[PDB]
Image (tube, coloured by chain):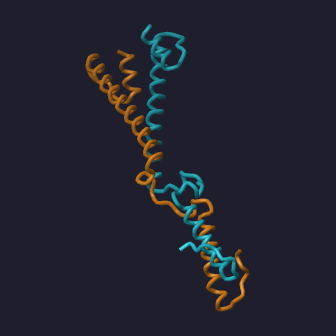
Chain colours: A cyan, B orange
Amino acid sequence: ESLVDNVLSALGLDPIGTIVDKILDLADEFGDWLGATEDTAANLSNLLTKLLSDPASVIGPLAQSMITGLTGALGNLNTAINQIGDVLVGTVVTPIN
Amino acid sequence: ESLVDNVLSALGLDPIGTIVDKILDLADEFGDWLGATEDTAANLSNLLTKLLSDPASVIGPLAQSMITGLTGALGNLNTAINQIGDVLVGTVVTPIN
């Protein structure tokens, strides 16, 4: 009885009733435990597979600054375009390349 | 014996044999439980660490449209180049900037 009581207390349910009822509650708790474990494993596997194959749905929008050098390249191109525009009207500026 | 049988049924295995055999099967089932739990935890930790450090292998290819403003910046640059090409031969167009 004490083994059943301590196990049920550890797993969460409050044991009230006969030993048979406590054993049935313990079996139901282990069933829920199995469900939780299997669902966690399946979710992890599915998330891994989706992140490998199609990351668009799982991953939300992200800032350009997270990409390495994207902001630098965009700034370089924009400054090159601006310098191309400016030289034709004057305002001598340091060339980029 | 009913506690043993109900626990075994909850964990999945069908209890057939003596009490000793059922207990041994129960012990093997908990060993597999331990393996599953530890493997799930280790896989989650490894996935988190790899996704933090090197996201290349884990994350598959993704569409440019997922990045915020990347398609807009590329379109703006391409339209600027096209306008630069067009103005020199005519076809008056609204300047971008």
Q: Quadrant of the N terminus of chain B?
A: top left
* Quarter location, residue A88: bottom right
Identify the residue at image location x=45%, y=57%: B60
Q: Quadrant of residue B68?
A: bottom right
Q: In the rendered image, which quarter contains the C terminus of chain B?
A: bottom right
Most extreme residue toward the bottom is B89
Identify the residue at the far top of this view: A2
Which of A32 and A92 lies nearest the eye of the viewer? A92
Nearer-the-camera pick, A57 or A30: A57
The number of callouts visible is 0
- Please tell me in which quadrant of the rendered image residue B93 appears: bottom right
Q: In the rendered view, tell whether residue A31 sits above or below residue B42.
A: above
| Picture layout, residue A64 above or below residue A3 | below
Q: Left of A51 or right of it: where is B81?
A: right
In the rendered view, would you say B90 is above or below A22? below
Q: Nearer the viewer, residue B26 or B15?
A: B26
Q: Position of residue B42 (x, y in %)?
A: 39, 36
Q: Left or right: where does residue B88 sit relative to residue B15?
A: right
Q: Position of residue B44 (x, y in %)?
A: 44, 39
Which x, y percent locates residue B35?
34, 31
- Residue at 49% x, 10% y is A18
Q: Residue at x 48, y 33 (%)?
A: A36
At horizontal 41% and vertical 36% (from top left) the residue drawn is B40
Q: Is residue B61 above or below residue A12?
A: below
Image coordinates of residue A77 in percent, x first then y, are: 58, 70
User: In the shown orientation, is residue B96 left or right of residue B14?
Assistant: right
